[PDB]
Length: 243
Ligand SMILES: CNC(=O)C[C@H]1COc2cc(F)ccc2N1C(=O)c1ccc2c(c1)NC(=O)CO2
Image (cartoon, rainbow, N blue to C red; front, side):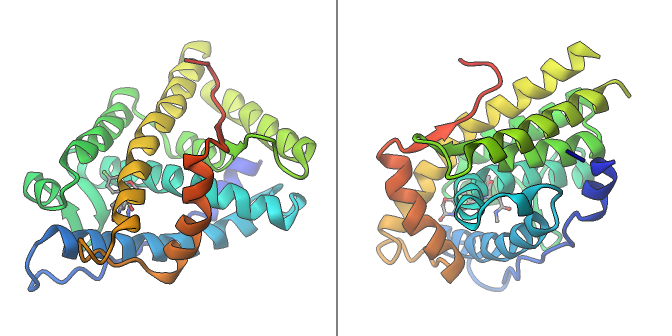
């Protein structure tokens, strides 16, 4: 099929500023609008990374779009836990160099309990001493962790790519079975947090002007397609270990 991990380490996206206006009042509407603008910028970076991701080109265009749309919150959350861990030792939520959440911002964002759930994942990075190599393989597994209920157009092609990245994670943990299951348990726990993040995101999207929450064009497109699929139960989370 294929070291692809050496490739993963080099294709990691550059740093993205939030463009946060600290002179503006710290309302839920202003903070969430800034987070949505940041999410739009990260999405462009995800597409650029996915195009050069080994094996991703083999999947048909329709499947590539489905995977990116279904996994956007999973990839975003996981990357947030990594930045929080790397830059603050998981003491704060490191959204961007210019946007680091303390207790105050967690309350102001009107997402306090969700922010705490996210901080719990970053605390697991500290407990496990997650490595950058482990992190890059796991991010690929998250891109390949949610599919349509009726499968993808090229299901066999997808399964081959996913299986090969799982083999890469197993090879990596040796540098071992105990660590492999600690990492798969961490990946599985991403689905529950992402579910709660999407529930709130769908809510603010469906009544955005009523709460003054702005969404960039990229998020409008992704959410408009994803929202009816997720609520109709057409999304299928892939678990290593069924709950
Ligand atoms: C730009 N963002 C990120 O870097 C990280 C990502 C995903 O992990 C999150 C965790 C968290 F604790 C708070 C926010 C986010 N992030 C979000 O983008 C997001 C999620 C839900 C939303 C919104 C954003 N926006 C809304 O209007 C309301 O629902």
